Structures are given as structure tokens and as C-alpha cells.
Image: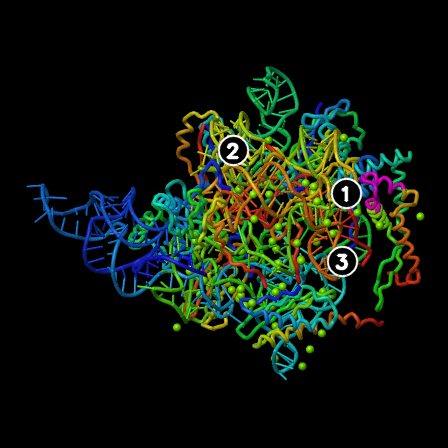
RNA sequence: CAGGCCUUGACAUGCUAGGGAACCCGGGUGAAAGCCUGGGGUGCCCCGCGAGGGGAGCCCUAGCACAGGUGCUGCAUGGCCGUCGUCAGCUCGUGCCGUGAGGUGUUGGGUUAAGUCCCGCAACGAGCGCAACCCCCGCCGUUAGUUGCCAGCGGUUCGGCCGGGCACUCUAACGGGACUGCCCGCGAAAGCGGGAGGAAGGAGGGGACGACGUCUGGUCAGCAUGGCCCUUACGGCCUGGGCGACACACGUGCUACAAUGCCCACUACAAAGCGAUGCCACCCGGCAACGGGGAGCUAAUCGCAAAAAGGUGGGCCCAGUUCGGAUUGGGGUCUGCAACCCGACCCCAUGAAGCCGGAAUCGCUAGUAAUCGCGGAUCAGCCAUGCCGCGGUGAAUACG
């Protein structure tokens, strides 16, 4: 009756529970659209199931913490796509080719000494 | 002027701290100060003995100082004469229960701080620095080391123009973490000035 | 400025001499190093010599210069201009 | 760079129209990494051009792009003791970049007070063949033809 | 903006509080 | 029946978190297994050279690793036997209830 | 404008003005002298005159050395000229083919 | 003016403001770490030796 | 720097002689330092029912050695660092060639991020570098389950709060994992191009790491150290001043010139850290800075804490303005013995230049740049717009 996946992006972690139904979606105690209200980035989160037509087929209970809304959005995108592969193993094809099943390791590069930021160097006047 | 200290680079990999204990924020400094004063006294007194390492331990109001040395006898004395004398000089300073151990240095010619001090002694005796350095390295390799490198910098032989002389044999892979390399430094005070002596001994890789 | 909850600061050793001169009738010159002391109503009409690091500067206190500090009237830098 | 021909970043298709070209345009609008702002401005503009002229915004946008693409450009090359403006064909990748760049820049030289509006209107003119954006393209091309004589210096 | 004390943004940048940025 | 372990070396910490958890599991009954409390890291950043050369540093850190073990069903069989256990030097123990 | 530094030395406004009249020879080439910077210094062997100047066609960096501070300055000028003349004419070399 | 200063820094002052940390090792008044009682140079010198408990080269 | 003072001296080791030791507490003079001085009881092993007699526990007073010097020399030096340069290099042993400096190897063909590796070769090996071994991050597992978590069932004061559980998240120790290993193709090989599998692919991203040497590089002011120089002073204490000066000139930065913006109000989403004369919930007084109450937290418990950009609404309407927030007036707060020179903060008023910057010039190749805020060391307070970290949002472009 329940289906699960773990999404991570940057510093955001999302626990997502897929349970069949009509499509209601909840993030941390609120509707999807309540929590991501005013964010174009949002509907990208529901993209894995749109790939396998599970759009309206599932309700989703979802936790989210750490990072920021966009990273959280990307985290969700991952987990619910793990949940789908879990809900059906043959879902891998038509999910892996969209690279929805992979986690990007791109995170904040550390601040280095001698620099102003990670790579931004201090301005020098040779002469 | 570049190279990283070969010991600090290997702490908790091939090499272990010399003051092993825990202390909280309010206390750390005071223990550390006493720790260094312990080393201060012992570094002067135990020099003639052949001091290589000085390990220090702490629990609560009690501390155990383990002295590594080439000449254990010069530390202990006659049946415990100096060894007893030490605890009193010690726990006077410490002001607490100061356990003093001694332990053998199995091969002083495989102990880098020892090799270093010996050459420093040799060059305060106006010996031929280059001949000395080749010797030191020859000793360390004979004693079985996988490699050795010894360096002397300063007014060598009294010359006005400072120079650096070194010699090496076998392997000394200072870039390799898992390579065990003992390192030691010795200061040679002369009439014309200070010479620095550095000894690298490659015991083997782990 | 200094908290009103706290005092109106005078170095006591400066102040004491003021009241001493007030009683007997003022005034001799008062050499002080107390730049930090407030001019206080009791000081008015006196002339206090304020050390600026080098010289003691004679300052005749008036009704206008009460609220201030003693240092404010013995400038510490010699500047006559540039070029 | 020196070693190899770098890899063109594949963009993620935009949420509303599913278009890599739209995404690219958004980023060009985007100042200070405020993409939400950037997204609104375009989509707001997409709303406006529909009100003013009832068509498909997507159709307008894409038509405006094809109109600002320089097919030929000049690139300098100092041959001998003089810098010749050599006429060159523009790679399709570069045609795109220049088109989207000029579109936004010309947009933001316009006098009306809101960005979405400027972005709207410029896309309307460029679709019809007017506006500073197309002027840029026309000019770049004219320079190229003007120096057709140096087209053998092409590398 | 960030340089004006009499505004919210200015008090943030400066890391203080007051009428224009209360806690 | 709380035991809180704090050391600068985690090999000698996990060493001792193991042995306390073994000792009271022997003389029973229940040891709540060694929970690894998040580490508090104290960093020191220094200029390598003694004079100028600001843009060149070296990073040093001091890590205090924390462990927690709970002996649930105590039975002073454990309490007395615990009083003598071979604890390394780089570790500090706290017991509370 | 033009900056002059006298490292661990005292000099006069006169001497400073002298240097300015000496650098002035570079005005010959009718090109922009941007932030010329002269550093006067004393070694055991003699004086050292350093200079870094930027121009639309590159930088000039030169060091002059001599027992006589004025000669040291003059040689600095000589080295600077030779550089400036190369900067201003090197491009003309390959006008053909 | 040095040894007199490493001394005057020890004696308690006339006012508690005038107190300031000196490096207990070399007497340095600047860049003195409270936690160690050491300056940045000594901090580095002892740490490289391994004579600072738990302290190690930090890399991430 | 000025002025007021001290002379084995603020500090080490001494040896000698007087005092009493030792430690505390006041008085005078003074800006303070210092000078002056009035207090008060010294254990010991000792002849001690007795004056009395010490020794050295530590001080005091007078000496003599000596101290002390951030005085000079980084061109006498050690140490440590900067730089070329994370560049791919620098050499040695033996043999061979050359009268000799020196060559060879190390060159050559291919290849690599690389003196990387392959093939060839009067060269055959070896070392220091390269790489790897180490740390962080990305997937997964094992072991653990509180102070952390809450899928499901009960209570639910309406808050993971309670029962309960450790699944999940996490936290932090140990492992697994990628090797061009596998298929297609080119290759003499080394490798290169493409594919699949996979969280990850051809060093996965970042870090630590810097060869022989160069710059007679930097530091005698962090420390050490040769030598030269000072000795009622080139040593030492104090009060005050200065290091904050201001016709000018350059370097690094902050905030800006505005509508992709500014202002108000409401409403979300981090990480890493720090915290017992500390971090401060919550309450109340104040427009506020702050003040007075007062709980919690040796802190995965409690606190700093609110992250900001964002989101939702409302105002501004292109103006030197509801842009900008300099300058100055006035009133207060807090730290501190003390904010005149010379602190930070709050409030009222003032509301400058600045309409995007000449010649010239800096950074950055992807979670980068840009932009947004958060922390920490130092620290009574702070002149931090600095520095070292931390996450949020998140591009453009590379023909060559
Ligand atoms: Mg929405
Ligand atoms: Mg960042
Ligand atoms: Mg620089
Ligand atoms: Mg643009
Ligand atoms: Mg244009
Ligand atoms: Mg037209
Ligand atoms: Mg304003
Ligand atoms: Mg800097
Ligand atoms: Mg000048
Ligand atoms: Mg000067
Ligand atoms: Mg001068
Ligand atoms: Mg030079
Ligand atoms: Mg000439
Ligand atoms: Mg020439
Ligand atoms: Mg002096
Ligand atoms: Mg000194
Ligand atoms: Mg202080
Ligand atoms: Mg200090
Ligand atoms: Mg030098
Ligand atoms: Mg040196
Ligand atoms: Mg110098
Ligand atoms: Mg010949
Ligand atoms: Mg021969
Ligand atoms: Mg040869
Ligand atoms: Mg040979
Ligand atoms: Mg070579
Ligand atoms: Mg060669
Ligand atoms: Mg080759
Ligand atoms: Mg490389
Ligand atoms: Mg090799
Ligand atoms: Mg060969
Ligand atoms: Mg993590
Ligand atoms: Mg488990
Ligand atoms: Mg490849
Ligand atoms: Mg390496
Ligand atoms: Mg020099
Ligand atoms: Mg010195
Ligand atoms: Mg010296
Ligand atoms: Mg002599
Ligand atoms: Mg003073
Ligand atoms: Mg001052
Ligand atoms: Mg200054
Ligand atoms: Mg001038
Ligand atoms: Mg200017
Ligand atoms: Mg600044
Ligand atoms: Mg500037
Ligand atoms: Mg305007
Ligand atoms: Mg105005
Ligand atoms: Mg104007
Ligand atoms: Mg205004
Ligand atoms: Mg005022
Ligand atoms: Mg002040
Ligand atoms: Mg500009
Ligand atoms: Mg701008
Ligand atoms: Mg220009
Ligand atoms: Mg790069
Ligand atoms: Mg901004
Ligand atoms: Mg900050
Ligand atoms: Mg702090
Ligand atoms: Mg502070
Ligand atoms: Mg100021
Ligand atoms: Zn120090």
C-alpha cells in the first residue's frame, strides 16, 4: 500500500511516500502549491511520474528539510522517482534515460584562503 | 622556502601525538603549559642521556611521562638515584602525582632526532661538515633504514657566505603519506653563528 | 556620550583642588593632566592649565564651555596648513 | 580553450512550454541569479503579447528569434599592417546566442517602464521585423557584405 | 539601500535593531 | 544510568564505548548501544609565515567526538565491576542518571 | 600623477624633483605614462633605482644600480627608454609580408 | 622593550581593561589564541611537532 | 613624542653583610609612577619553666658580578614563509663518446593532466618530483537510537506532546563501490573515440600535498643566533599626547547612481559554528539603542536564531526622486577607571556627491561567476565595509 524514496539535492533531503489515489500532494504539512507558491521551479518536481503517466494515479506524502526551496524541489524529483522504480522495477527504463533516477553531486565548492570566494581572486594592480 | 613538516603531515596516519589526553576549553591551555615546562626541564636534564621522544599522558590529577632514550642508565642512575631525584624535581613543578617512566630506544642510529643531534655535536666540535653528513647517512643505512637524508644550513666551516649541504641515500618519499619517516632537528651553536641540522630517516612504508 | 545613569565624571583630584580654591577664594593656576574631566559649574572663572602631551595650555573657563571636556580646549596637534 | 572544443551546455526545457530556447532566453533575462524574477518577466511578457496581439506567444518569440539571427558577421584579423574586417558565416549555436543577447539588450534600451513590457514589445517588433534588435542584425550583415572582398581571408 | 540606517535593509547589513527593524 | 564519552581521538573513543557497552551487557541486563553524538569541531587558521604573506594559510582543527551509552537494567553487579575498567588516556567519561 | 618612494632613506623635495625631470625624458615618445612609480633604495654596493610604468602598449620595469644615486637614476632611465622604444616600434617590424 | 613587557603583562593591572594576552611561549602580544595561550606562530610550531593534543592538519 | 620619576634595576643565576622574614592593612605627598611612612604575628631542628643563640624556608636594605636593549647588520645566520609553479621538471650510479668544458641516459615516434605510459635507441638502472597512500563531498551497506527521527496503531491539553518504535531522516565510526573492468571501433603497444551498466566514468568534484633550485626574495620587530653598539640609559615605571594629522598622490574594498528597483506589512526555505563574572528564552518599561525582572542550557536537550534574497499583498511613477545615505546639528544608550583628541549603537532633524565612469585595468570555465544572507577567530567595547569559513539562489560563453 505504501511506496518510498529518498531524494537529496545540495543540502536538501526529502522523504517521499507514494500512496495510490487521486493526486493530492503534501509537503511538510501543506499542499504542494501552498509550500511552493509562486515558484516556477515547482512543477518540475512532479516530472518523474509524468514520464510514466502516474500523474493523477498517486497521492504523495512528503517530508522536506535543509537547503532551500529549489534544492528541495530537486530532492523531491529524485525521491518520487526512486519510489516509482520501487513501485515497479521495470520503471527504470523510461526513467533512467531522463536521468531522473540519478543524484547530481554538484554542491557548494568550499571557500579557499587567498580568494574572496571559492574561485574569485582578489584584484591586484601589477603596475 | 616550501616543504611541509614531515611529522605534522603524518599525525594520525604514521605518527602519533606526544601529548595524549583530553581536556576541556577551560583547562586545555594550563595543561599544555605544564606539558611544555615538563619538556623544558627534561630536554635540558636528559640531553646527555640521548633524549628522542617525550610522551605525556593525563587522567585526573595524575600524569605519566614516558622518556625514550638511547642510554636508559644515564636517566635512572645508580639503583634509582637520578630516577628518584627526577620525581621530586618533577612533582615539585607539576604539583601533582607525576609518574616518570623510561623506555629503550632500540636503535639510536635509526632515530632521526638522535642522528640530528649527533651531527650538530660533531659540527660544534669543528668537524668537517660534509664528511660528517655522509657518515651520518652511512650509519643510518647500515643500521638498516630504507633511506636517509641529512641537511646542514649556515656558515659552514665558518664561511661568511651561508650555504646548505645535504646528502641522501636510498628512498625518502616525503610526498607519500603511508611512508614512515622519522624526522628530527638539532641546533648547533658555534662561535660564528647558528647552524641548522635536519635528519630524515625512512624506516619503511606501512 | 557617557551614560546619564552613571556620573558626571571629574577625576576627583582635579575637582578637589577646585573646591579647595573656591572656599578660600580663588585662584592660583591649576596644572592638570586630566583631559577627561568635564568642565563643571564650580570650575567657571578659573584658569586651568591643560597638558596636551607637550605643553600645559592655560584655559579660562566660562559659562559657555561648561558641558564640555577639558581636552577640547587644549588641541593636541600643531597644524598651520600645507605647502 | 587550447586542448579540445568545449561542450555546449544542454539546458533544461522550461516548465510552461517545454522549450530549451525559452530557458536560454530566461537566463539571458536573469540578473543576479534571480531566475524566479526572470521567469515571471518572460511569462508576464508572454501574457502581454497575447493581449495586444492574440497569437501564440511561443510562435511570436520563436519568430522574433529567427529574425534577429545574423547569418553573416565580420570578425577582425590583422593581416600585414592593417586590421581587415573579415566576413564570416555565423555558426547556428552563435546565431542563437547573439539573437537572444540582442533581444534582451535592445529590450532594455526601450522607454516603457516595466521589463515584462519591454521584453513583450521588443519580441513583437522583432517578430514583425522592426526594433533595435533587428537593426543590430541588419547592420552586422551589412558590414559583412560591405567587406565581401576580404572573404578569401576567411579561416 | 544597505547603507541607510533609517531602513530595515540598513539595519540588517549593519546587524543592529531599532524602530526601523524591531525584534 | 547515563554514560557520556568525550575524546579527541575516535579510535580510542569507540574503543572505550565498546568496552563499557560490553561490560554491562555481560553482567546485564540492557545496554542502550553507543550512540555517536555529532562532533564539535574547533578550527584554527594561521598564516604560514611569521611576517606578511597574508594570502598563505594553514588549517588546523581540534575534534571533540562524543559518544553516549545507556545501561538500562543496571543491577549493581555492573555498577561495582564498572568502577574498574581499563580506559585509554585520550578519553573522558561522565556518569549521571 | 607620479609617485616616488624612498625606501629606508630620507630624500629632499629637490631630489624628488630631479627624478621627475629625469623621467621626463620618456615624454619624448609622446605616449601616456600611467602611474609611474620610482623606488629609491640603498644597498651596501650603492643605490638602487627601481621603476614600474604602464603605457597603452605595455609595462616598463627597470632597475638601475650605481654608487652615485644620480647615475643609478640615469641608468634606470636608460633601461626604461630602451624598453619604451621597443614597445613603441616592435609592432612595425613585421608590416611585410 | 620586550622582557619587561612579557613581565608587565603577567602582573595584575590597576584596571582590568589594561589586561591583554601575550603568547606564553614567545611573548608575542599579537594574534594570541585564548584556547592555547599561544600565538599563531607557536600554534603552528607545536602542532607540527604533535605536541598539541588532538590538533591535526585540517583538510576538506 | 613631551613631561614626572627608578639604579643589581619590571626579570635570571650568584656570593657577601644588616633587618625582620615570609603576608596583609591603611597614612602623607603626587596626574600617576615614585618618594615618605604609621600598622601588625615567621614556622623549623633547636639550650627553650629563662632572657637569649641560630639555620634556611621568603622578603627587605647596601654592595659587587650581572641583568635589560622592538639599538645596527635578513649583505654574517638558524627557523618559517613568499615566488617562479602543481610548472614537469632536477639529477645520480656504472658503462659509452669527447684532449676538455661536457654529451649520452633525460633525445627520438606515439600517448598522457604529468620525465604518464608505450615503442625504439650505447645505454642499463636508481633517486627527488608526477601519481597513489590521507581529508571533505556524491551512492549504498553494516553497527548504533538520544538530547535526533515519526512511516503505522493507540491517546493527542490541541506542540513528536504522550504511549511506543528506530523504520525513515539524521548523526558518526567501519566497510562496499570505478579498474578503461565490459562490448563496438582504431591501434605495434600505450592509449583514444563511442556504447551499455551505474549514484558516480575515464584523475567523479574539491582539499591536504610544492622537486633540484632561483629571486645575495622576505622576516635580527614572533622566536633563536654570530658580531657591533647602549649601561643613573639606546634599560625600567608612570601620566598625557601620538600611531587616527591632511594642499595632495596610488593600491584594496564598501555603498551606490535606481522600476529585473526602493519602501511598508504579513509569510516561508539553510549550513557551519559559538556559548557558566557565557549564550539568553519568556515578561515588563522605553519609538528605540537599551534597561530591570527571570526560566533553560557543564548544551544533537537550552540559547545566539530572525537567515536574506524569495513568496503574498499594499505604496512609490522616472523626478537627484519614497533613488543615494555622505555631511552636520540635537537628544540618548552601552562598554570601560576614562570615549576631548579617539568607540560602537539608537532616535529626531539635516539629506552632499553620484544619471553608470578617460587613458588604462581585474576576476571567473559550473553549482563557477554574479547576487543573498549566516557564523567564527581577535575581542571590555570596537572603528570588520577586513579576514577565514558556511549555506541560499544560480547564469553566460570557449570558433580557435
Ligand atoms: Mg504556483
Ligand atoms: Mg556560496
Ligand atoms: Mg599583492
Ligand atoms: Mg544581456
Ligand atoms: Mg544593440
Ligand atoms: Mg527594417
Ligand atoms: Mg533611502
Ligand atoms: Mg587579502
Ligand atoms: Mg611620491
Ligand atoms: Mg620613513
Ligand atoms: Mg624622503
Ligand atoms: Mg628589484
Ligand atoms: Mg639616451
Ligand atoms: Mg631591445
Ligand atoms: Mg624605550
Ligand atoms: Mg627579546
Ligand atoms: Mg585588552
Ligand atoms: Mg593579545
Ligand atoms: Mg635572505
Ligand atoms: Mg633566511
Ligand atoms: Mg629588507
Ligand atoms: Mg669536439
Ligand atoms: Mg675519457
Ligand atoms: Mg656528464
Ligand atoms: Mg654518466
Ligand atoms: Mg633534464
Ligand atoms: Mg640533459
Ligand atoms: Mg618522446
Ligand atoms: Mg600536472
Ligand atoms: Mg616516471
Ligand atoms: Mg630511452
Ligand atoms: Mg553530510
Ligand atoms: Mg538501523
Ligand atoms: Mg577518455
Ligand atoms: Mg602527490
Ligand atoms: Mg636583501
Ligand atoms: Mg632577534
Ligand atoms: Mg642580532
Ligand atoms: Mg670577537
Ligand atoms: Mg601612556
Ligand atoms: Mg593614544
Ligand atoms: Mg597605522
Ligand atoms: Mg603629489
Ligand atoms: Mg584618484
Ligand atoms: Mg572597505
Ligand atoms: Mg576603489
Ligand atoms: Mg533616472
Ligand atoms: Mg537633493
Ligand atoms: Mg549633480
Ligand atoms: Mg531621498
Ligand atoms: Mg551629535
Ligand atoms: Mg575615543
Ligand atoms: Mg561599469
Ligand atoms: Mg549596476
Ligand atoms: Mg581602454
Ligand atoms: Mg580553470
Ligand atoms: Mg543588491
Ligand atoms: Mg558576517
Ligand atoms: Mg564569537
Ligand atoms: Mg568582537
Ligand atoms: Mg571612525
Ligand atoms: Zn608565540
- Residue F12: x, y in percent? 48, 41
Asked if disc 3 and disc 2 are in contact, CB closer than 8 Å, the reply is no
Q: Which chain carries label 2?
A: F
Q: How far apart are marks 3 and 2 (CA)?
A: 55 Å
Q: How far apart are marks 1 and 3 (CA)?
A: 30 Å
Q: Is residue H49 visible?
A: no
Label 2: which residue?
Answer: F34
**Dominant secondary-structure state across the stretch colored magenta:** helix
Question: Looking at the rendered structure, which numbered label has been put on residue D30?
Answer: 1
Please give left or right for residue G12 compared with residue D145 in the image.
left
Asked if disc 2 and disc 1 are in contact, CB closer than 8 Å, the reply is no
Please give left or right for residue B179 compared with residue I35 in the image.
right
Residue I123 occupies quadrant: bottom right
Asked if ligand 56 lies within 8 A of label 3, the reply is no
Please give left or right for residue I283 compared with residue B31 in the image.
right
Which quarter of the rendering shows the N terminus of chain D?
bottom right
Binning the other alpha carbons within 10 Å of mark 1 as few (below 14), some (14 to 19) or many (20 upward) gives: some
A92, A113: nearer the viewer: A113
Q: Which of marks 2 and 1 is in front?
A: 1
D66, A4: nearer the viewer: D66
Mark 1 element type? loop
Location of residue F66 with respect to H19 vertically, above or below: above
Q: Distance between the residues labelled 2 and 1?
A: 51 Å
Q: Which chain carries label 3?
A: D
- Residue I267: x, y in percent? 67, 28
Binning the other alpha carbons within 10 Å of mark 3 as few (below 14), some (14 to 19) or many (20 upward) gives: few
Magenta residues? D106-124
Indicate yes or no whether the magenta region holds residue B204: no
- Residue A121: x, y in percent? 66, 53
First along the sequence among labels 1 and 3: 3
Q: Mark 1 lies on which chain?
A: D
Amino acid at each position: 500500500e505504501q511506496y518510498y524514496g529518498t531524494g537529496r539535492r545540495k543540502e536538501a533531503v526529502a522523504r517521499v511516500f507514494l500512496r495510490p489515489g487521486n493526486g493530492k500532494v503534501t509537503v511538510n504539512g501543506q499542499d504542494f502549491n501552498e509550500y511552493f507558491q509562486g515558484l516556477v521551479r515547482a512543477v518540475a518536481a512532479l516530472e518523474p511520474l509524468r514520464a510514466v503517466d502516474a500523474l493523477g494515479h498517486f497521492d504523495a506524502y512528503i517530508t522536506v528539510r535543509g537547503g532551500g526551496k529549489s534544492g528541495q524541489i530537486d530532492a523531491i524529483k529524485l525521491g518520487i522517482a526512486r519510489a516509482l522504480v520501487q513501485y515497479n522495477p521495470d520503471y527504470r527504463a523510461k526513467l533512467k534515460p531522463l536521468g531522473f533516477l540519478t543524484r547530481d553531486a554538484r554542491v557548494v565548492e568550499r571557500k579557499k584562503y587567498g580568494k574572496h570566494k571559492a574561485r574569485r581572486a582578489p584584484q591586484y594592480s601589477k603596475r | 622556502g616550501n616543504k611541509i613538516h614531515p611529522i605534522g603531515f603524518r599525525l594520525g596516519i604514521t605518527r602519533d601525538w606526544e601529548s595524549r589526553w583530553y581536556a576541556g576549553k577551560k583547562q586545555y591551555r594550563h595543561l599544555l603549559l605544564e606539558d611544555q615546562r615538563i619538556r623544558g626541564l627534561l630536554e635540558k636534564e636528559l640531553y646527555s642521556a640521548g633524549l628522542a621522544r617525550v610522551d605525556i599522558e593525563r587522567a585526573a590529577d595524575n600524569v605519566a611521562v614516558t622518556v625514550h632514550v638511547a642510554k636508559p642508565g644515564v636517566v635512572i642512575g645508580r639503583g634509582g638515584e637520578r630516577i628518584r631525584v627526577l620525581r621530586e624535581e618533577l612533582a615539585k613543578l607539576t604539583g601533582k602525582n607525576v609518574a616518570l617512566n623510561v623506555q629503550e630506544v632500540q636503535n639510536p642510529n635509526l632515530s632521526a632526532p638522535l642522528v640530528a643531534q649527533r651531527v650538530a655535536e660533531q659540527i660544534e666540535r669543528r668537524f668537517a661538515v660534509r664528511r660528517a653528513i655522509k657518515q651520518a647517512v652511512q650509519r643510518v643505512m647500515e643500521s638498516g633504514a630504507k633511506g636517509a637524508k641529512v641537511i646542514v644550513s649556515g656558515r659552514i666551516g665558518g664561511a661568511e657566505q651561508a650555504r646548505t649541504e645535504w646528502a641522501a641515500q636510498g628512498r625518502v618519499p616525503l610526498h607519500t603519506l603511508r611512508a614512515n619517516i622519522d624526522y628530527g632537528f638539532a641546533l648547533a651553536r658555534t662561535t660564528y653563528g647558528v647552524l641548522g641540522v635536519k635528519a630524515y630517516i625512512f624506516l619503511g612504508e606501512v | 556620550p557617557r551614560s546619564l545613569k552613571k556620573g558626571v565624571f571629574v577625576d576627583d583630584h582635579l575637582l578637589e583642588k577646585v573646591l579647595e580654591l573656591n572656599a578660600k577664594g580663588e585662584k592660583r593656576l591649576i596644572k592638570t593632566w586630566s583631559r577627561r574631566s568635564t568642565i563643571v559649574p564650580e570650575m567657571v572663572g578659573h584658569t586651568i592649565a591643560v597638558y596636551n602631551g607637550k605643553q600645559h595650555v592655560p584655559v579660562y573657563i566660562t559659562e559657555n564651555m561648561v558641558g564640555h571636556k577639558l581636552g577640547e580646549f587644549a588641541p593636541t596637534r600643531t597644524y598651520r596648513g600645507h605647502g | 580553450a587550447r586542448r579540445r572544443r568545449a561542450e555546449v551546455r544542454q539546458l533544461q526545457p522550461d516548465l510552461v512550454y517545454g522549450d530549451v530556447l525559452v530557458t536560454a532566453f530566461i537566463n539571458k533575462i536573469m540578473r543576479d541569479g534571480k531566475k524566479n524574477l526572470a521567469a515571471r518577466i518572460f511569462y508576464d511578457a508572454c501574457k502581454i503579447i497575447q493581449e495586444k496581439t492574440g497569437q501564440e506567444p511561443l510562435k511570436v518569440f520563436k519568430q522574433a528569434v529567427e529574425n534577429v539571427k545574423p547569418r553573416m558577421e565580420v570578425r577582425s584579423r590583422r593581416v600585414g599592417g592593417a586590421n581587415y574586417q573579415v566576413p564570416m558565416e555565423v555558426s547556428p549555436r552563435r546565431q542563437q546566442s547573439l539573437a537572444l543577447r540582442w533581444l534582451v539588450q535592445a529590450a532594455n534600451q526601450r522607454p516603457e517602464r516595466r521589463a515584462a513590457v519591454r521584453i513583450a514589445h521588443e519580441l513583437m517588433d522583432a517578430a514583425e521585423g522592426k526594433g533595435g534588435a533587428v537593426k543590430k542584425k541588419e547592420d552586422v550583415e551589412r558590414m559583412a557584405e560591405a567587406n565581401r572582398a576580404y572573404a578569401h581571408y576567411r579561416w | 539601500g544597505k547603507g541607510d540606517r533609517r531602513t530595515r535593509r540598513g539595519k540588517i547589513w549593519r546587524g543592529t535593531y531599532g524602530k526601523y527593524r524591531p525584534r | 544510568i547515563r554514560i557520556k564519552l568525550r575524546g579527541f581521538d575516535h579510535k580510542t573513543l569507540d574503543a572505550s564505548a565498546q568496552k563499557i557497552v560490553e561490560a554491562a551487557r555481560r553482567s546485564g541486563a540492557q545496554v542502550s548501544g553507543p550512540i555517536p553524538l555529532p562532533t564539535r569541531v574547533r578550527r584554527f587558521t594561521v598564516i604560514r609565515g611569521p611576517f606578511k604573506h597574508k594570502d598563505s594559510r594553514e588549517h588546523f582543527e581540534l575534534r571533540t567526538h562524543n559518544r553516549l551509552v545507556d545501561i538500562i537494567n543496571p543491577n549493581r553487579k555492573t555498577i561495582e565491576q564498572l568502577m574498574t575498567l581499563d580506559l585509554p588516556t585520550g578519553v573522558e567519561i561522565e556518569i549521571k542518571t | 600623477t607620479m609617485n616616488i618612494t624612498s625606501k629606508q632613506m630620507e630624500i629632499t623635495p629637490a631630489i624628488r624633483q630631479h627624478v621627475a625631470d629625469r623621467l621626463a625624458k620618456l615624454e619624448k615618445w609622446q605616449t601616456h605614462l600611467i602611474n609611474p612609480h620610482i623606488i629609491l633604495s640603498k644597498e651596501p654596493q650603492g643605490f638602487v633605482a627601481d621603476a614600474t610604468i604602464n603605457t597603452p602598449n605595455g609595462v616598463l620595469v627597470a632597475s638601475g644600480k650605481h654608487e652615485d644615486m644620480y647615475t643609478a637614476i640615469n641608468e634606470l632611465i636608460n633601461k626604461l627608454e630602451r624598453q619604451l622604444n621597443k614597445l613603441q616600434h616592435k609592432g612595425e617590424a613585421r608590416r611585410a609580408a | 622593550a620586550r622582557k619587561a613587557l612579557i613581565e608587565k603583562a603577567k602582573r595584575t593591572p590597576k584596571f582590568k581593561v589594561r589586561a591583554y594576552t601575550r603568547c606564553v611561549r614567545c611573548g608575542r602580544a599579537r594574534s594570541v589564541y585564548r584556547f592555547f595561550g599561544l600565538c599563531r606562530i607557536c600554534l603552528r610550531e607545536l602542532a607540527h611537532k604533535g605536541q598539541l593534543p588532538g590538533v591535526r592538519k585540517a583538510s576538506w
